Amino acid sequence: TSEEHFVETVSLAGSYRDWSYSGQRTELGVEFLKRGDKIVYHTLESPVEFHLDGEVLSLDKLKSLLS
C-alpha cells in the first residue's frame, strides 16, 4: 500500500527533490521520477512496482535513490 500511496504523493506534487514527474504513459505503463540519465517507472497493475533500467526494487530502496 505504501508504494501506491507514495506514487500518489508525487503525482499530486508534479515532482520530487530534484526529480521531475512527466506522466509519460509509455507502452510499459508510465514514467515516474526523472533525474539525469535515471528514470524511475510505475506500472498500472501491481498496483504499482518500481523499475529502474530493468532492475525492479522496493519502496524502501526507491526512497533512498530519490533522496
Image (cartoon, helix red, strand yellow):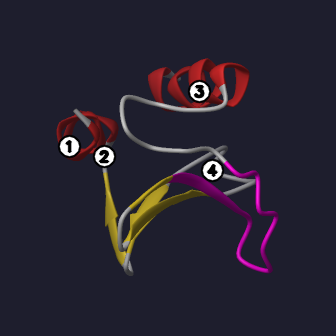
Marks 4/3: CA distance?
18 Å
Label drawn at residue 58: 2
Q: Cβ–Cβ below 8 Å for labels 1 and 2? A: yes
Label drawn at residue 40: none
Q: Which residues are magenta?
A: 22-33
Helix, strand or loop at label 4? It is loop
Label drawn at residue 46: 4
Marks 1/2: CA distance?
6 Å
Q: Residue at x 75, y 54 (%)?
A: 44
Q: Give the main secondary structure of the magenta stretch.
A: loop
Q: Quadrant of the C terminus?
A: top left
Amino acid under label 2?
A: Ser
Amino acid under label 3?
A: Val
Q: Earlier in the sequence, mark 4 or mark 1?
A: 4
Residue matched to label 3 = 10
The reply to whether the magenta stretch includes residue 28 is yes
Q: Cβ–Cβ below 8 Å for labels 4 and 1? A: no
